[PDB]
Image (cartoon, rainbow, N blue to C red):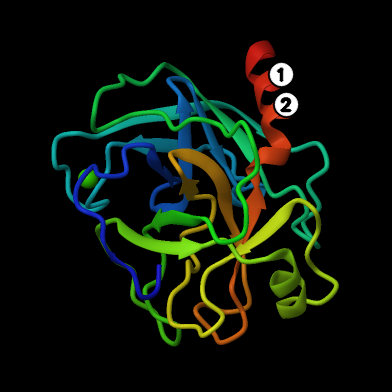
Amino acid sequence: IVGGYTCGANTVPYQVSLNSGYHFCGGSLINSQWVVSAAHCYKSGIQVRLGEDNINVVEGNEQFISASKSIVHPSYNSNTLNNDIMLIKLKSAASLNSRVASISLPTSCASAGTQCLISGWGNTKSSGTSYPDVLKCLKAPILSDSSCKSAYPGQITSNMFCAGYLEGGKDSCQGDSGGPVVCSGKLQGIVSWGSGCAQKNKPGVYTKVCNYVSWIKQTIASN
Ligand SMILES: [Ca+2]
């Protein structure tokens, strides 16, 4: 996250870190046994880390649970990033409380102008590299479809939305991928892609979770 603020320990209780020896992507806990992330985050041998603030220090609220099954969306296209969404089932159910909690799936799609919270352990610089040890947060609005399409001609599908600031300076970034965009207490987005980070006229692009609720629910019910 570029231009954000330090969240504070366990203030984002649904945030997960996906670990394969090192943090590589974010995700969101949607019930005690299932995590949603980006399809482009797919790897074999994932450990999900819940209750994290500093990802390099054991602070006492962590739960580490291996993935038993990963399911990339049937229509994921890695060239276009259309349908950039994946489900991860945990080998055992997490223990839920105030510091580790699930986030609700949306009933409806959020509108342009809605303020959302985006979080993760990704790069904090628009040029150069600096990865934080603690979780960072950013409040950003959903942009209109017209402004999103004008920023990225020919690249925005009905399964994506833009959020952020056209002036630049504030955005998600590499390493935030797969993480949550929460608006009005509901999961509306997954951190997906963007051209660099925090560049002028190049906002973040997010997977539009409201289009996937049927597939998520049906999948969970049968796996
Ligand atoms: Ca920790």
Q: Report the residue that reaches farthest toward the top.
A: 222
Q: Quadrant of the rendered structure where residue 16 is?
A: top left
Counting from the top left corner in percent of width and height, residue 203 is at 59, 74
Q: Quadrant of the rendered structure where residue 134 is?
A: bottom left
Decide if residue 192 is on the left or right side of residue 155.
left
Q: Residue at x 67, y 66 (%)?
A: 144
Counting from the top left corner in percent of width and height, residue 4 is at 33, 69
- As rendered, which of 183 and 27 lies closer to the eye? 183
Decide if residue 207 is on the left or right side of residue 130.
right
Mark 2 nearby-residue class (10 Å; few <14, some 14–19, many ≥20)? few
Q: Amino acid at mark 1?
A: Gln
C-beta proximity under 8 Å, tags 2 and 1: yes
- As rendered, which of 58 and 202 lies closer to the eye? 202
Q: Quadrant of the rendered structure where residue 72 is?
A: top right
Counting from the top left corner in percent of width and height, residue 139 is at 39, 62
Quadrant field for ligand 1: top left
What residue sits right under mark 1 in the picture? Answer: 218
Q: Quadrant of the C terminus?
A: top right
Query: Can residue 195 be seen in the rendering of this structure?
Result: yes
Residue 11 - label: none
Query: Can residue 72 be seen in the rendering of this structure?
Result: no
Vertical side of 221 occupied by 179: above or below: below
Mark 2: which secondary structure? helix
Mark 2 or 1: the one toward you: 2
Q: Amino acid at mark 2?
A: Ser
Q: CA distance from mark 2 to mark 1?
A: 6 Å
What residue sits right under mark 2 in the picture? Answer: 214
